[PDB]
Length: 496
Ligand SMILES: [Ca+2]
Ligand SMILES: [Cl-]
Image 1: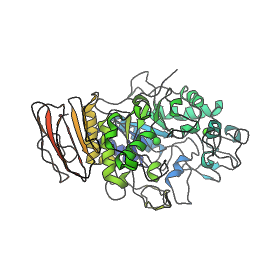
Image 2 (image 1 turned 90 degrees about the vertical axis):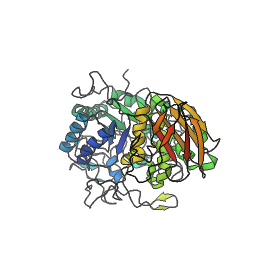
Image 3 (image 1 turned 135 degrees about the vertical axis):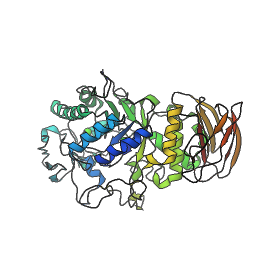
Image 4 (image 1 turned 60 degrees about the vertical axis):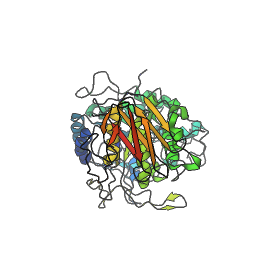
């Protein structure tokens, strides 16, 4: 039995970023910035040939309808993909492919992003090739429309069609061989791993058979005898017949409870309290940290498609709370952390649903994607926000230390350290707090890395609101003056 939940990073790097709908040429350039800020890797949008949808015009979700396993996509050509992987790998920033193996397209016919035909009505995908024998059908699914409705029926969830997406027969030797060939081709070029889409809709045994066909990582960059990193998108918020714990033996699993819980806590939904995070992690009924890929939001649930709709998940639209939740997640020790990196779109919530949730990335038209320019009102670039990247540095400095010196106000203020390496005071109250705490840190002069550029004087005021220096006393205590409001947190850490 091979296990795929271990990932590989350069020393001092750990956090990964989803550069959602970024072009390969932009990711290739971004790898320098990411390396300089000690991020470990990038999840890239599905790079295989996908459906081109023109009604509505070029939505993001067309990339979740495979047409073939060639490598010309909205983000760029095979040549551009391979240039990106090579450059990023040489910089020590690795690439995880969003791998879409559960299904092909929905109904209708057309061509994909590399010119190959699809026909979801006849189940013909000549670019693979797949035909009807390669799919589940009326022999395998008994619902009246062929779609999934009863999430208490694992057979229905796995063998019927997710919203009409034609469902591949993952038990078939041919499908397993074809999908492994796709993954192995990408591994051979230098891809480090995969985010596997829609895994709740596949049988773990079929995933095991596909993963057993995989070659090990390319030793131009990776250690000999290393399996690819696999993290599996399994949406499991409890009370269903498919469980995230079915997939952890194969690799890591997305823990959607993490962002649900942190979102509810930071929003103070239904009387939640920041102080309740004292035991956050597996003890909240979540996966063990070692089995989990964690994140505040993803591309689906920032569009209201997760549970609670728009009322729980935090996103760049709620920037102040989003930074609080992300800072906590990065300072804590639980899971492999992925940060979303988003684009803006005309979100328009009507009766709880965003009417414009289909809108694709910044475009001049014609299905192209604009070059990224961070902070221009179109590309959000959360991973480049100082509050994020300085908390990634905090996370890196703190690595391997326990949570220590926990404090809270019984309510909406907590503070904790990571050994003798870092300390964060989070005041989520509607009033200011002055509090002296054992920070666990060596005595000295520290800067708040939430508001300042550097961890020690000179503090650096590029953001314009760098707070006064924090003095840690000789006994390890420090006095935190934390006003409520924007960025209502102070994080300090020893020199990297
Ligand atoms: Ca399926
Ligand atoms: Cl995901």
